Length: 465
Ligand code: HEM
Ligand SMILES: NCc1ccc(-c2cccnc2)o1
Image (tube, rainbow, N blue to C red; front, side, top):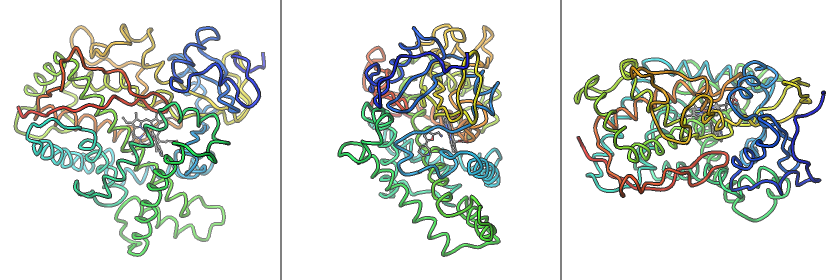
């Protein structure tokens, strides 16, 4: 046809705003999908976006035409501070350069090796101590979990972990939680459409920018310190490595290795490597309390395979199919980044029967793939069986795409999975979960859903076993 995917007729500037509920972007788009198809065009304010719903559409584009869909789209709130710099929100040469270096440097500091595994085990140990410190009292787990998670990636980029009593550390975690919630509210999704006006208007978006600026200032501060103490022969962390590469590229006019890309890339890892996993853990514990039978089987498998003495190690996952199914189901049900991070066609593209002009933005609806009724029998329920065969053995699914897929997929996936398995397992090994209310009354529906899926606030107690 040579034409863009079908979709509701947009109005000047506001686009399809009148046919969308900013507080429920996902449901609005899915409803529109019922009449236009799994592949349609939507106008988020002036942003023309091609929406991909369901496993087939998403995989066909991001994997089968991986290079064509390898461009990075926008996320207005984050672009406020990033401005196209850094590894995540960058495109072309800058993205290729920063991503290759980041993956390599991450591996140099233990990611994927025994080095980081030991780091996660030790930090898991610190979480256990902290949980024991609550004396079984009812608590908000939120920051107990984010502190532990953040310390893993923090060890890599800053060279050392934060003290759990570090007030400034708590401030930063609050900033990350704040930005994740904002981008998932009605105002945050409205911002994605009308940032051209809103970035200049009073409102919640301004407070959001301040949280981001607070994070950037902290990073800039850390970089400055490392600069005034850098050992070119012995890098201490991710920042040092980049600083070294920068020195080596000082004679290259068009190098991508300069201060701003260092600050933004480090900020990317600090935020991206913290809040995502933290959120998953938080939702996970809530779901396990909502389903005692699942916790029971988890404990059964842990006691048998690992016991009550030694610390869980990453290799234990191979001998624990149920736990593997449980973590997968948590990520599937959790649907933490419901619409992924926007992609964009790098050149004129022919997708299925449509035409996508170069630069077109793309919304891979990851949540629609994680609940694709063709891949999971009861997508709306939380059931580990979704990842298990009759034999109780772990069964993979092509529809398991919480980290997205393709050329700009999450390269933090390996670390994330090691953290999820080690933290979930070490916690369940040591504690029994006690909810504030009867299971049947626990609400596992999300508090907010926009850029991310945010679970409702809750308290709980960790009872030693
Ligand atoms: C449960 C945890 C996590 C989830 C659900 C998650 C999810 C995602 C998603 C959906 C994307 C976009 C993929 C795409 O464009 O196709 C992504 C990007 C990215 N993630 Fe994660 N992530 C997680 C953890 C991590 C961790 C631990 C790190 C940091 C070490 C990290 C770093 C990144 C980076 C740097 C990108 C941008 C990649 C690029 O543009 O080339 N993520 N993540
Ligand atoms: N790891 C995926 C993910 C979710 C949100 C973000 C993020 C947000 C702000 C800056 N850099 C990365 O990254």
